[PDB]
Each structure stands twice: as C-alpha cells, then as structure tokens.
Image 1 (cartoon, rainbow, N blue to C red):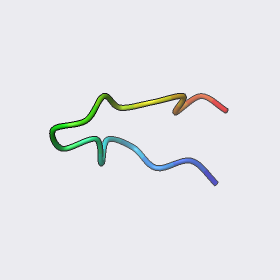
Image 2 (tube, helix red, strand yellow):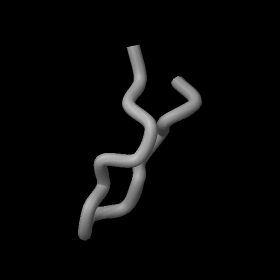
Image 3 (cartoon, rainbow, N blue to C red):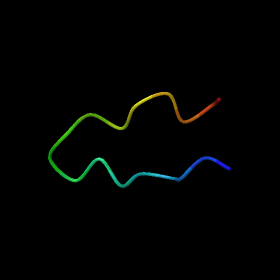
Image 4 (cartoon, rainbow, N blue to C red):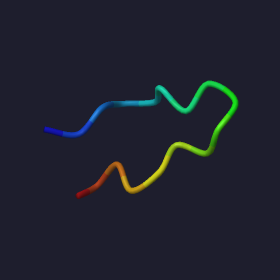
Length: 17
C-alpha cells in the first residue's frame, strides 16, 4: 500500500505505485 503524502521535507515519491 502507498502512503498519501508523508514526504514531509523529502519529495512525495512514487505514490501511484
């Protein structure tokens, strides 16, 4: 399962898959 945002001060990342 993905996340939603998280990234905080990172860069979201491949949330789609």
